[PDB]
Image (cartoon, rainbow, N blue to C red; front, side, top):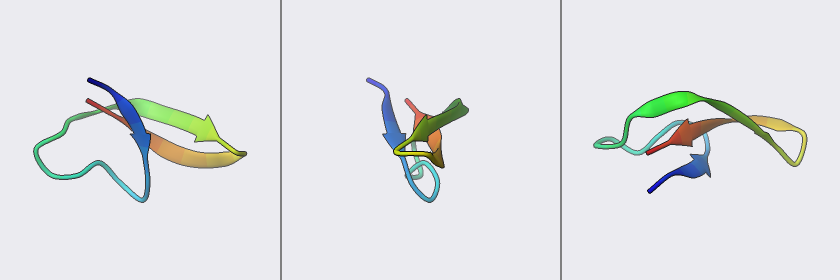
Length: 30
C-alpha cells in the first residue's frame, strides 16, 4: 500500500516520485 510521507520513506518502503501535500513536497512511498 502507498502513502505520502515526510521527510522520507520509512526504510523497507520504496519511493515512487513525490506528492505535494498541503503545499509541501513529500515522498510517495509504497
